[PDB]
Length: 283
Ligand SMILES: O=C(NCc1ccco1)c1ccc2nccnc2c1
Ligand SMILES: [Cl-]
Image (tube, rainbow, N blue to C red; front, side, top):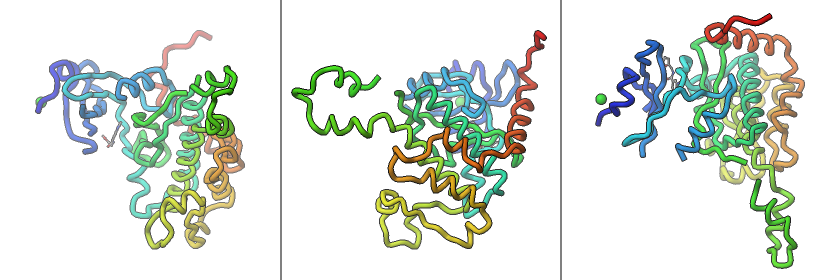
């Protein structure tokens, strides 16, 4: 195989980043980029990502629809968050706070703008730099959904002929976004402990059973090096009933996140990236 003439005309292709993500160079700027190849839902992913504009959400620079789909993204020099947590690697409580706060802001943004990621994992969280204190970006919107429903339209009529299950679904409705709060809860547990909450390692109970019951594997020795504020937040996010489960808003109001130094550090990392783009001010 070869890359399209159109892609080749703007970008110089180099080393593979993840076997599909490649490193390329924009000919115009000589700046480095990341080119995501999705082999022939991608039109929706582009449509979502072109509209979304937030520091903690990955931006589309360019797109090519050929024998395969080619997506040009900003290069995240720190790689995946997954690589920082593999093999029971533990992140300092302060680095968890910084990263998590950014994931909360990013997800709040998505939900405010009616998008549900649906696939939040440490492998979809990208670190901006090789340094511990850095900006994080949420990637991979392949699985995302966009929120007026068929239920809202149905309820405008009289339920003479309406099925009972439809009327029952009304209670639970409009809480699909709560799936992302579960994921953040599972991510936060992994960062804080080095191990996952629900797993088939040294257990008799099925993975479906642990998750449905909401009974995560708790190892005191590991959680002793973690604060009660941190663990309280996990407990509040890893709630079975989605209606009772914490929202990004509630999470962002939690004592663990009321850390003026952490907020300052992110704000300081923000302007650090913004110095490049900065157009002279009016005043
Ligand atoms: O391996 C990566 N970074 C490490 C690194 C350092 C220098 C070049 O690469 C990597 C992987 C997937 C990505 N997907 C979208 C945007 N940036 C990405 C970066
Ligand atoms: Cl080629």
